[PDB]
Image (cartoon, coloured by chain):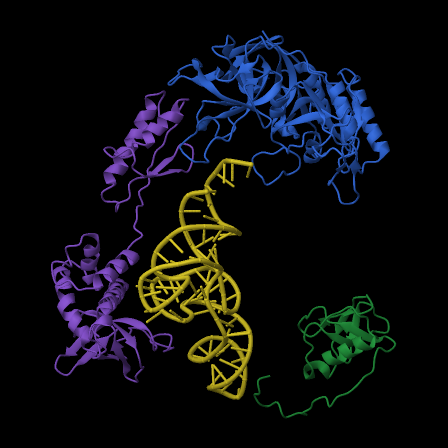
RNA sequence: AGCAGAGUGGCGCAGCGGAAGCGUGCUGGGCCCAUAACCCAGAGGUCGAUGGAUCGAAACCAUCCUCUGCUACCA
């Protein structure tokens, strides 16, 4: 069924297709960036340079990024072109192609149980759920994946509008399985060069105080990579909440060790 | 623990691992392993237990027989006795010094804390070989004469060649003690006559008088690889010094001071140095726990110093005294000295070169090996029997003892003379 | 060649197969060492003596003697260093001669 | 041992959320009177193990092992 918010493409929009035949006059191709509607590419507007081979360019069974040059709205002729394509558009379109595939796979679990004897089943599910998720956040550059990703980490998004059954478990499982494990790249940077002998116990007091105002029972990940370097991967959230945990903790270890003898790295 | 330190010094290409494993049973090993471009060029460590079945031969644990594995060309077998437990005679310690000429300053340092030696001669090269003489002379200067020459590589060397070599060495060294030192030819490819070596080292080398009552002094020569394992970091519960003690029974929990010191921040001169103080965590020797560390033995003293001082070999030739030791920490020093009339440690097949070296000139950098310390320093005043030297890093002078003085002849320093501090 | 033309005005051909002199007196088997130009060429004899081989009439552009391979060489009656090519063989013929045991068993093809 | 890569389906390099990806080679065909250049065509097959989501996993994501790259120590 449709993979996109609108059924028909517009004018000058970047899309994706999959080649199913090669024509004399260009390439007649099916879309997989929308419905399986037909769109015709023309030979002239594929490149601005010569062309020796022809199967080392376009061939069957390839996703190809393209621009919709014209569309007949009533007839359903989607004129197409590969002449204006930049690699930056390919990154943006590959993401939207891949994200729609995963979102429609989530909106396939819904159809496994419900009445789907007719092809239009998924279309019924798509219009009513998809649009209110993505339309509210299309202007900021988000897909319906953002709405679902927000629901798993704070559940009020999918309870603000009609909640389905049995969907919720598989929805949670698939969001939490695929978009994790989930991750902190927090590493402490600490340098010490002691003349102390009481440094061994001094470091222990400093290590356990990586995060202030936490319980004595807080689990953390200590790492020793080299003798002066003390890496502490602090409490694992998303690395946008443990910023204060990373920054101010570094001051503790370097200060605690200077009090017991000599100068150290700051 | 240990009772005596026998050193295993010997010039290039005689094989160290075969002989060292036969005497101690503990491999000589160090950084870069790897193995060894030839023979060990690091300061190796090893201890061993010497027992008897009431026989001059020394057993293995399996004391019924011993079948070697030195070569599969033939089977070398020896018989120490038969089994029913063996009586412990003593615990011995070794000091494997560098076998290569460039490493002379290190060989000197390591040597200077031994109580006896084993000159490992190799029959492959020249008969009055440079390094044999170099070693021997240094040994008689430091205060030892408990030497057992060992002909360590005469496996394929014919009996005329090997006979000529022992003769020429013993005839060149006509002014250095060596006539009361035995010369034991051995095999190192079939480990033969090893049993008779065991008889020699208990005969020629008893325990010399050790002063327990006198104040502890530990001379550290080797650092420690502590720490960085797990679990619980960082840096360590600290740092281990491989040192021998030459005076005093160092007891566990005692505080010890490393006396060459660390220099004060923003010094405009050559003074001031401040000793570092560390409490003794543990007194480990062999593989057996101890509460004491008797003198005359090479012991691993774990102390409460932190990883940076032991992360590399940086505690070579440091003097440690318990605690607030009286020994002066000179930065500029008054050497009395004398020179050899030959250049020691160099002499090849053809007169080229080895003769009389010219007199020292002021503002030249020379290695003064004082104690086990190795510092570099420049000569500020040069009279024949009174030179004044200024040293880069301060030297703790335990006693006025001896010194060894070397001059940069070419690529590296070479031994020119000795003397005594005033 | 790759077909072409003007290659039929002249006597096709071929080696209807055939057979088999030797050696004779100063007329023996050698192996091509190098492959000079102009015309001449190098070839070490199978006995042990080196020599420099020379092409012979007819065999000029009527038979190509690629590098490496047995070949029949007359020796000059008086000259040592330079020698004179005869009568080449076939690689199959050379391995049959080797299997017979008449030339020395030292060179590979 | 910290970090990185990989654990062939011809080779070599190993590409990404669709079951050989890229470059190359070998073998065959085409073009040409012929060669080169140029154009096409190939090939038994969980891609080290133990698991989860999945329609499916070298490849989506984990838990383990091994080999190496850089850094580097316990031994």
- Quarter of the picture holding the C terminus of chain B: top right
Q: Who is closer to the viewer here, B357 or B179? A: B179
Where is residue B11 shown, x and y percent of the image? 70, 30
- The chain letter corresponding to green is C
Where is residue B251 shown, x and y percent of the image? 53, 15
Count of picture labels: 0
- Quarter of the picture holding the N terminus of chain B: top right
Q: Is residue B169 above or below residue D61?
A: above
Where is residue B327 shown, x and y percent of the image? 52, 9
Q: Who is closer to the viewer here, B108 or A178? A: A178
- Which image quadrant is residue D56 in? bottom left
Q: Is residue B34 above or below residue C26?
A: above
Where is residue A178 shown, x and y percent of the image? 30, 58
Q: Is residue A151 above or below residue A164?
A: above
Which shade is chain A?
Answer: purple
Q: Is residue B157 left or right of residue A4?
A: right
Which shade is chain B?
Answer: blue
Residue at the farthest front position? B84
Q: Is residue B326 left or right of residue C84?
A: left
Please give the name of the residue rendered at 21% of the width and 76% of the height, measured from the top-left corner: A116
User: Do we see residue B36 in this rendering?
Assistant: yes
User: Do we see residue C90 in this rendering?
Assistant: no
Which shade is chain D?
Answer: yellow
Please give the name of the residue rendered at 72% of the width and 78% of the height, measured from the top-left corner: C91
Q: Who is closer to the viewer here, B29 or B160? A: B29
Q: Who is closer to the viewer here, B55 or B348? A: B55
Please give the name of the residue rendered at 36% of the width and 28% of the height, measured from the top-left corner: A203
């Amino acid at each position: 069924c449709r993979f996109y918010q609108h059924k028909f493409p517009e004018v000058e929009d970047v899309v994706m297709v999959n080649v199913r035949s090669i024509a004399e006059m260009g390439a007649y191709v099916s879309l997989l960036e929308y419905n399986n509607i037909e769109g015709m590419i023309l030979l002239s507007e594929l490149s601005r340079r010569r062309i020796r081979s022809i199967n080392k360019l376009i061939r069957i069974g390839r996703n190809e990024c393209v621009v919709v040059i014209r569309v007949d709205k009533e007839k359903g002729y989607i004129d197409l072109s590969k002449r204006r394509v930049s690699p930056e558009e390919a990154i943006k379109c590959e993401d939207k192609f891949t994200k729609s595939k995963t979102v429609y796979s989530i909106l396939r679990h819904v159809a496994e149980v419900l009445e789907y004897t007719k092809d239009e089943q998924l279309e019924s599910l798509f219009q009513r759920t998809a649009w209110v998720f993505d339309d509210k956040y299309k202007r900021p550059g988000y897909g319906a994946y953002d709405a679902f990703k927000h629901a798993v980490s704070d559940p009020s998004i999918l309870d603000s509008l009609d909640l389905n059954e049995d969907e919720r478990e598989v929805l949670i499982n698939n969001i939490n399985r695929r978009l994790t494990p989930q991750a902190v790249k927090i590493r402490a940077d600490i340098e010490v060069a002691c003349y102390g002998y009481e440094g061994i116990d001094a470091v222990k007091e400093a290590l356990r105080a990586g995060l202030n105002c936490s319980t004595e029972t807080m689990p953390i990940k200590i790492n020793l990579i080299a003798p002066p370097r003390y890496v502490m991967t602090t409490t694992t959230l998303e690395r946008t909440e443990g910023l204060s945990v990373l920054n101010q903790a570094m001051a503790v270890i370097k200060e605690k060790i200077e009090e017991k003898r000599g100068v150290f790295n700051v | 623990q240990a009772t005596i330190n026998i050193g295993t010094i010997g010039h290039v290409a005689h094989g160290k691992s075969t002989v060292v494993k036969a005497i101690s049973g503990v491999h000589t090993v160090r950084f870069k392993n790897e193995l060894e471009r030839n023979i060990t060029i690091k300061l190796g460590y090893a201890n061993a237990k010497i027992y008897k079945l009431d026989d001059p031969s020394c057993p293995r644990p399996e004391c019924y027989r011993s079948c070697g594995s030195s070569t599969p060309d033939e089977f070398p077998t020896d018989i120490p006795g038969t089994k029913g437990n063996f009586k412990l005679v003593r615990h011995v310690s070794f000091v494997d010094c560098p076998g290569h000429d460039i490493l002379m300053a290190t060989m000197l340092n390591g040597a200077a804390v031994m109580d006896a030696a084993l000159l490992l001669i190799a029959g492959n090269e020249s008969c009055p070989q440079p390094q044999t003489s170099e070693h021997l002379a240094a040994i008689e200067i430091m205060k030892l004469k408990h030497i057992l020459i060992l002909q360590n590589k005469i496996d394929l060397v014919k009996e005329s060649q090997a006979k000529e070599q022992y003769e020429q060495i013993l005839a060149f060294v006509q002014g250095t003690v060596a006539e009361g030192a035995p010369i034991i030819p051995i095999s190192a490819q079939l480990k033969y006559n090893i049993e008779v070596v065991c008889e020699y080292i208990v005969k020629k080398i008893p325990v010399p008088p050790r002063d327990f009552t006198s104040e502890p002094r530990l001379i550290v020569i080797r650092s420690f690889d502590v720490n960085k394992p797990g679990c619980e970091v960082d840096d360590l519960k600290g740092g281990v010094a491989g040192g021998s003690i030459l005076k005093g029974v160092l007891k566990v929990g005692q505080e010890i001071e490393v006396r060459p010191g660390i220099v004060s921040k923003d010094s405009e001169g050559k003074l001031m140095c401040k000793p570092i103080f560390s409490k003794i965590v543990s007194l480990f020797a062999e593989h057996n726990d101890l509460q004491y560390a008797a003198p005359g033995g090479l012991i691993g003293v774990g102390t409460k110093i932190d990883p940076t001082l032991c992360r590399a070999d940086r505690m070579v030739g440091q003097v440690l005294g318990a605690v607030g030791a009286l020994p002066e920490i000179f930065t500029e020093l008054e050497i009395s000295y004398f020179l050899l009339r030959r250049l020691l440690g160099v002499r090849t097949e053809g007169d080229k070169k080895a003769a009389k070296v010219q007199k020292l000139s002021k503002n030249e950098v020379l290695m003064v090996n004082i104690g086990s310390l190795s510092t570099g320093g420049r000569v500020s005043a040069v009279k024949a029997d009174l030179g004044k030297i200024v040293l880069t890093n301060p030297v703790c002078t335990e006693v006025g003892e001896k010194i060894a003085l070397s001059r940069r002849v070419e690529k590296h320093w070479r031994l020119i003379g000795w003397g005594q501090i005033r | 060649k790759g077909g072409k033309n003007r290659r039929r005005g002249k006597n096709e051909n071929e080696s209807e197969k055939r057979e088999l002199v030797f050696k004779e007196d100063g007329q023996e088997y050698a192996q091509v060492i190098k492959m000079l130009g102009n015309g001449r060429l190098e070839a070490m004899c199978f006995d042990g003596v080196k020599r420099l081989c020379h092409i012979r009439g007819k065999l000029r552009k009527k038979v190509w003697i690629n590098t490496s391979d047995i070949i029949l060489v007359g020796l000059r009656d008086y000259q040592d260093n330079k020698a004179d090519v005869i009568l080449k063989y076939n690689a199959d013929e050379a391995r049959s001669l080797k299997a017979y045991g008449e030339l020395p068993e030292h060179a590979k093809i």
